[PDB]
Image (tube, rainbow, N blue to C red):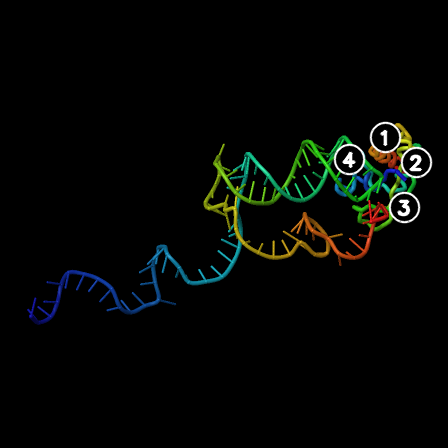
RNA sequence: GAUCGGGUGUCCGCACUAAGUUCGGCAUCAAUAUGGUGACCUCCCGGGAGCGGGGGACCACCAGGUUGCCUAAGGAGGGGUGAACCGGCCCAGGUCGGAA
């Protein structure tokens, strides 16, 4: 249950920094959903599970494309990292916004 | 002192003026030092979230301290709208995050 939280607004380049965005607009994607975040994180070897009805507090869009929250495992509960490539949440958010466009485009 | 010279201001659909009487049109500058506000961009740092700590970049408006290669004149006036989603703020309920 000590898994970090990642919203689709963290990688949304059509959102300002005050609207939820966590990475620059140069390395962010246009409208990533919580299923594109879980699929490209689980495709590198990460422990990710999807909470499809978990919305963002700063998100206002009541429709389905903007809901969702992905919960990623960084530590095996012994303090050690699951992968040495993902030590922080920012290395999980710069990887998913790099592999999401390879899916549909 | 009789007529009466010599000359003006009353009479005009008049000539030109320009203190007022009255309603409109157009128009109404910019740079500095200080602080403030709002946004936005980009980094670190902490967190299971809503979030919290910190470094810069840029934009507009704002207060008021000096000013000008500034005006035909350019107030640091007064007000109103700020909504059907675009100012900021305080935000009931609701609502999203939370075990709270």
Q: Which mark is residue A47?
A: 2
Q: What chain letter is assigned to the residue under label 2?
A: A
Query: In screen coordinates, is B6 left or right of A56?
Result: left
Residue under numbered circle 4: A24
Residue A100, how many percent across, how many down? 87, 36
- For marks 1 and 4, the one nearer the N-term is 4
How packed mark 1 is, by other alpha carbons closer than 10 Å (few <14, some 14-19, many 20 or more), is some
Q: Nearer the viewer, residue B45 or A78?
A: A78
Q: Earlier in the sequence, mark 4 or mark 3?
A: 4
Callout 4: chain: A
Q: Secondary structure at mark 4?
A: loop
Chain letter for the residue marked with disc 1 in the picture: A
* Front label number (2 vs 3): 2
Q: Quadrant of residue A16?
A: top right
User: Does label 4 lie on the same chain as label 1?
Assistant: yes
Residue B100 appears left or right of B58: right
Q: Are marks 3 and 1 on the same chain?
A: yes
Residue name at image x 80 percent, y 34 percent: A27
Where the C terminus of chain A falls, by quadrant? top right
Q: Secondary structure at mark 3?
A: loop
On the same chain: label 4 and label 3? Answer: yes
The x and y percentages for residue A80 are 89, 29
Q: Which residue is mark 3?
A: A52
Badge 4 and badge 2 both on one subunit: yes
In the rendered image, which quarter is residue B17 located in? bottom left
Disc 1 marks which residue? Answer: A87
Earlier in the chain: of badge 4 and badge 2, it is 4
Q: Residues within 10 Å of mark 2 (few under 14, many from 20)?
A: some
Label 2, secondary structure: give it: strand
Task: Pinpoint residue A98: horizontal percent, then vertical percent.
Answer: 85, 33
């Amino acid at each position: 249950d000590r898994f970090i939280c990642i919203y689709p607004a963290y990688l949304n380049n059509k959102k300002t920094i005050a609207e939820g965005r966590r990475i620059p607009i140069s390395k962010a994607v246009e409208n990533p959903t919580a299923t594109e975040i879980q699929d490209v994180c689980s495709a590198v070897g990460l422990n990710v599970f999807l909470e499809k009805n978990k919305m963002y507090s700063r998100e206002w869009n009541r429709d389905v494309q903007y809901r969702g929250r992905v919960r990623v495992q960084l530590k095996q509960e012994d303090g050690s990292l699951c992968l040495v490539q993902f030590p922080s949440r920012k290395s999980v958010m710069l990887y998913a916004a790099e592999m999401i466009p390879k899916l549909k485009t």
